[PDB]
Amino acid sequence: LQTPMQTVDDLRSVCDELPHSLETFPFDDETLVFKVGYLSKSRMYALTDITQDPLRLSLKVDPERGEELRQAHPQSIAPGYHLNKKHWVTVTLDGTVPAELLGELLRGSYLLVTKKGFTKAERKELGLPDSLEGGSHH
């Protein structure tokens, strides 16, 4: 099922299922970074500072959709914190944005990165998928 998308454990649970995903802490702080790709070439798709409660989740979004999201949830979705605000938003994980939407945005950020950061040949070699399974049924 849908986790509540409110803890690091919730985020791990989603990212652990995504092919070639890797956790690191490349800063000096407690910023957990999820990257996708080869061990010699991996690209960030989600970040959160694990010492903050509630967590803040940064992720990549199509610019148009980021604009919509920020208008639909202005108190909970901000331009990406210390990130390229053309492509990143930061979502407060306090229960104010539906878990199912959050899950999909997290999977979406991963997909976008595989599309933008890797070529068709790369995605074939490594085996990065065109779409993701384990969408929930309605």
Image (cartoon, helix red, strand yellow):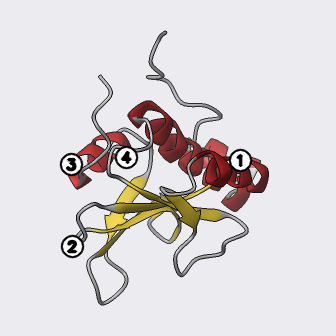
- Residue tagged 2: 51
Q: What SS does tag 3 mark?
A: helix
- Residue tagged 4: 15
Q: In the displayed image of the protein, which residue is found farthest to the top?
A: 138
Circles 2 and 3, Cβ within 8 Å, touching? The answer is no
Q: What SS does tag 1 mark?
A: helix
**Chain-order first, disc 3 or disc 4:** 3
Label 1 vs label 4: CA separation?
25 Å
Label 3 vs label 4: CA separation?
10 Å
Location of residue 51 with respect to 20 vertically, above or below: below
Please give the name of the residue rendered at 65% of the width and 75% of the height, measured from the top-left corner. 84
- The mark lying in front, picked from 1 and 4, is 1
Please give the name of the residue rendered at 48% of the width and 46% of the height, measured from the top-left corner. 106
Location of residue 44 with respect to 6 vertically, above or below: below
Q: Is residue 127 left or right of residue 1?
A: right
Residue type at the position of mark 4: Cys
- The mark lying in front, picked from 2 and 3, is 2
- Residue tagged 1: 68
Q: Kindly identify which numbered label has been placed on residue 14.
A: none
**Chain-order first, disc 2 or disc 3:** 3
Q: In the displayed image of the protein, which residue is found farthest to the front?
A: 75
Circles 2 and 4, Cβ within 8 Å, touching? The answer is no
Q: Is residue 49 left or right of residue 21?
A: left
Say which quarter of the image contains residue 47: bottom left
Label 2 vs label 4: CA separation?
19 Å
Location of residue 99 with respect to 120 vertically, above or below: above
Please give the name of the residue rendered at 50% of the width and 57% of the height, measured from the top-left corner. 75
Q: Nearer the viewer, residue 23 or 85?
A: 85
Q: Nearer the viewer, residue 33 or 125?
A: 33
Q: Is residue 12 left or right of residue 125?
A: left
- Residue tagged 3: 9
Please give the name of the residue rendered at 78% of the width and 51% of the height, measured from the top-left corner. 64
